[PDB]
Image 1 (spheres, rainbow, N blue to C red):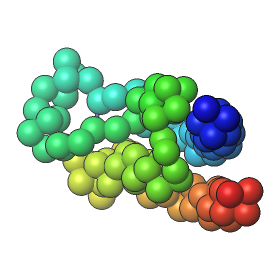
Image 2: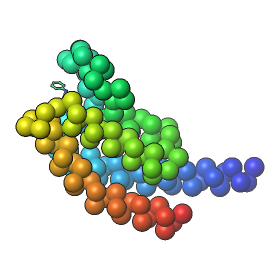
Image 3: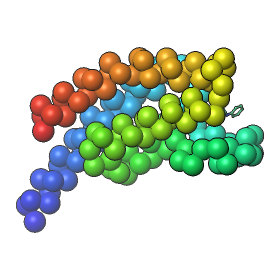
Image 4: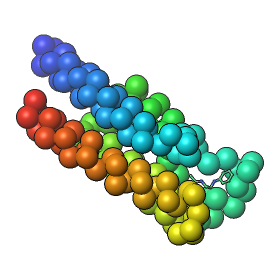
Length: 121
Ligand SMILES: CC(=O)NCCNc1ccccc1
């Protein structure tokens, strides 16, 4: 139907927009600490601690599969990355500190993204 095409045109642009947001967020992780899923070969006990793992590569896969219906779903996953890290790692680690910085620096980008998504509809 013409409707479903229109719906799919918007989803495509939401995806285009989120792709830009994603690059900007990941630019704030220069050490690439959150770039890939935590390896179970390197951290065997990880899933005993963290029930819903997340990282930028996994978000990107879901993104290109147009798996985010809105910004809120996208933000949930970004928050997972941060919150998981701040629990698994103690406060005085490079890991925890990287999460704090990514959260702080990401807030700017996500504040703008909300206003654009709302604006463009
Ligand atoms: C994002 C995160 O939680 N990173 C710290 C836990 N993962 C880890 C993996 C390999 C070597 C050392 C640590």
